[PDB]
Picture 1: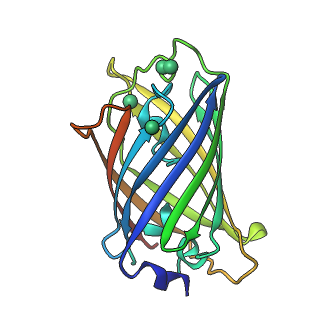
Picture 2: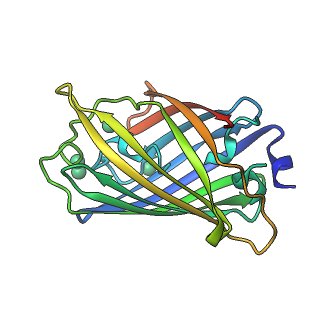
Length: 219
Ligand SMILES: [Cl-]
Ligand SMILES: [Cl-]
Ligand SMILES: [Cl-]
Ligand code: NA
């Protein structure tokens, strides 16, 4: 039933409230997703001024229901949706804790996020804005989390640093349905995401334009 909500192009709205080392900020994003081709197109702005962290560190936080149709937990949870929570551990640096609700509100798929970052170095790669404006593709293994009627995933993200090094970000993820309704649990499978970051030449606010392709593969 939920998968039928994704037969065409679906409008997306994203809202994030963040606090990293006491630096508070908010983000709004808008665009669309197409599960037929696994394509996401979104623009995000910081609505509070300068973004105090690099845009690439927010990519994974800022809708896996759009993975290209190859049983899908993320789609079957809709329209009631799912909670997505992560801890992201930046090597030699701080950690993010995120909680989000992803659900339909009318025709729009809405991702509403709270993010708290702690224990960051003010001069490190994150708060010091030392990361390149790109995002390395990753193949993520999605597994059933039977004890919570949802899924889990653990994976590394490597952010390119402006000195040629990499900043590792260990991701720990758990998703659980919001509704009491039935949901499909997937076979363990991989999602390949490949991302292109760009700028809107007419946007004066701190912002990110994002194009992503998400494809699924079995075992
Ligand atoms: Cl604004
Ligand atoms: Cl800043
Ligand atoms: Cl950035
Ligand atoms: Na700032």
